[PDB]
Amino acid sequence: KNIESLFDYSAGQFEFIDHLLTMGVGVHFAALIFFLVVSQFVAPKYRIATALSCIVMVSAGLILNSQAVMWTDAYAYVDGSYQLQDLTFSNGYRYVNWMATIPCLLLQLLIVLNLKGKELFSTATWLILAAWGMIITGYVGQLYEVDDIAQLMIWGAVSTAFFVVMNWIVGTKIFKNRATMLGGTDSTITKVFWLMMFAWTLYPIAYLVPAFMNNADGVVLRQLLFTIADISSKVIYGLMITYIAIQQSAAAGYVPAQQALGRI
Ligand SMILES: *C/C=C(C)/C=C/C=C(C)/C=C/C1=C(C)CCCC1(C)C
Ligand SMILES: CCCCCCCC/C=C\CCCCCCCC(=O)O
Ligand SMILES: [Cl-]
Ligand SMILES: [Cl-]
């Protein structure tokens, strides 16, 4: 049901996709160790924001790892090209994983925005419901990326509605609570918003690849887009969230944070 199944791949195409996913694994697990060791310099009220980056690194790292082994499982070099065998490859498992990873990305944002208690719970709940609506309708949509492009588009429109509403909640909370933020991170958080808008928008672009580039090179392009998007939305994003957590920790008088920033 996925366009990947439609084509044979050159050694070049096949190896490049393998390398993309493997590099993705390496980058996420490398970052994981960074978030782990810096977590001790985060104040208790923000430390979970850095823990969530660890959780995202392993979750995303495992899905990329799974995609890579699925890739090599599904294809074998036969008569001069990589051809589909008995096992299958699908991006559908990415969508399932988003059900967990996207709430984590959203939660660590709310935490460094200094949301607490009832507002935290209510905002998270609405955000997670919006995200799940987006992911599920998008998941259903890509089931038709071969059989019914029209249906892919309509489900994608519904998904984009959830996407836009979710982004509006994110933007609203960021620009409203920006003033509460310490150590100059009121400026930093604005770049985080635009990073999210940029990086997250790469995913619906990848979703539409079967509509504007239905060939083996389009398959490569989609994986390339996922790689840019994953690294930007999880790794670069996590580094900024953690930077914001440490800076605010130091500004609130957390001594390990102050000492850590002093060494650099
Ligand atoms: C780490 C993974 C992330 C941040 C994934 C984010 C995914 C999206 C923003 C997906 C958006 C979609 C649309 C807005 C329309 C097409 C269907 C989706 C689910 C791909
Ligand atoms: C934050 C951005 C992260 C970027 C990650 C991607 C790094 C490698 C990107 C690709 C370089 C272009 C490779 C050439 C493609 C050759 C075409 C092919 O052989 O199929
Ligand atoms: Cl604290
Ligand atoms: Cl993920």
Image: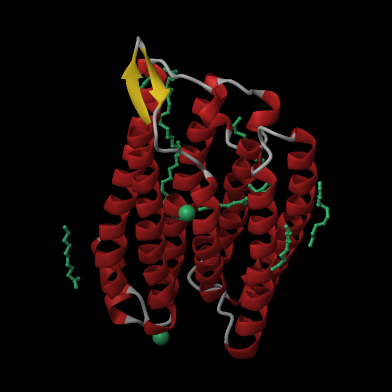
Left or right: where 105 falls relative to 142: left
The residue depicted at 61 percent of the width and 56 percent of the height is: 193
The residue depicted at 36 percent of the width and 52 percent of the height is: 61
Left or right: where 86 falls relative to 221: left
Occupied quadrant, residue 22: top left
Left or right: where 241 falls relative to 113: left
Total labels: the figure holds 0
The residue depicted at 52 percent of the width and 30 percent of the height is: 4
Left or right: where 75 falls relative to 141: left
Residue 88 pos. (x, y %) = 44, 38
Above or below for 149 versus 116: above
Name the image quarter holding the C terminus.
bottom left
Residue 207 pos. (x, y %) = 64, 39
Name the image quarter holding the N terminus.
top right
Q: For the view shown, which residue lies furthest in the front direction? A: 86
Above or below for 17 versus 216: below
Residue 14 pos. (x, y %) = 38, 24
- Between 56 and 197, which is closer to the camera in this rendering? 56
- Between 109 and 66, which is closer to the camera in this rendering? 66
Q: For the view shown, which residue lies furthest in the bottom direction? A: 117
The residue depicted at 49 percent of the width and 61 percent of the height is: 101
Residue 136 pos. (x, y %) = 65, 58
Task: Tell me how the rendering is colored.
Answer: secondary structure
Occupied quadrant, residue 248: bottom left
- Between 33 and 243, which is closer to the camera in this rendering? 33
- Between 264 and 127, which is closer to the camera in this rendering? 127
